[PDB]
Image (cartoon, rainbow, N blue to C red):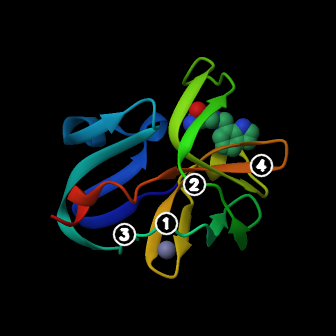
Amino acid sequence: SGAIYVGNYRVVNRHLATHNDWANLVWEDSSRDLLVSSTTAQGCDTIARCDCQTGVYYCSSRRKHYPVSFSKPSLIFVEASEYYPARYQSHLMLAVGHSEPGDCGGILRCQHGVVGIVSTGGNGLVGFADVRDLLWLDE
Ligand SMILES: NC(=O)[C@H]1CCC(=O)N(Cc2cccc3cc[nH]c23)C1
Ligand SMILES: [Zn+2]
C-alpha cells in the first residue's frame, strides 16, 4: 500500500485505486500502472525533478528502507498478474532488492525528493513507477 501527496493530487498504483480515486479521476495510465486523483486537503510531498539513479525505497514486507541503484525509466516486459495480463509496462525503473505484491505503493526517494512508487517485483528485483516526468503535479 501507499500514495504520494503533492498539492491537490493523490498518486497511487492504478491497480490499487479506490472508488473515491475513480470518482475524482484526474489522470490514469494502465501501461504505467499509475492513477492520479484529486484531494480537498493540501499535500506536502516534494517530487524530484532529476535523472538520479540512486535512492532509498520503503519495503513494508520487511519494515525497512533500503538504499538502491536503479535503471532509467523504460519499457520492461512484466509477467501476468490478477490485475493485468502479461504486457510491457512503460516508465519502469528496476533495482536489485526485495519486493512482494503488497509492497506496491512504497515510495522511492532521492536527495531531490520522490522519484516514484513500487509497482513490480520477483526474482530478487523491484520495479518502480516513475513520477518525475509528470511536471503538472506542481501546477
Ligand atoms: N505493475 C504490475 O503489473 C503489478 C500488478 C499487480 C502485482 O501484484 N504485480 C506483481 C508484483 C508486484 C510487486 C512485487 C512483486 C513480487 C512478486 N510479484 C510482484 C505487478
Ligand atoms: Zn534526484
Q: Which residue is mark 1?
A: 51
Q: Which residue is mark 3?
A: 47
Measuring 65% from the left and 47% from the top, which residue is drawn there?
102
Q: CA distance from mark 2 to mark 4?
A: 15 Å
Mark 2–mark 4 CB contact (< 8 Å): no
Residue type, numbered disc 4: Leu
Q: Earlier in the sequence, mark 1 or mark 2?
A: 1
SS at circle 3: loop
User: Residue 63, position in %: x, y?
Assistant: 72, 69
User: Residue 100, position in %: x, y?
Assistant: 73, 47
Q: Mark 3 or mark 2, which is nearer to you?
A: 2
Residue 101 in sight from this viewpoint: no
Q: Which residue is mark 4?
A: 125
Q: Earlier in the sequence, mark 1 or mark 4?
A: 1
Q: Earlier in the sequence, mark 3 or mark 4?
A: 3
Image height of 56 relative to 11, above or below? below
> Does 119 sit left or right of 116 as displayed?
right
Badge 2: how crowded within 10 Å, few (<14), some, or many (20+)?
A: few
Q: Which residue is mark 2?
A: 72
SS at circle 1: loop
Residue type, numbered disc 2: Lys
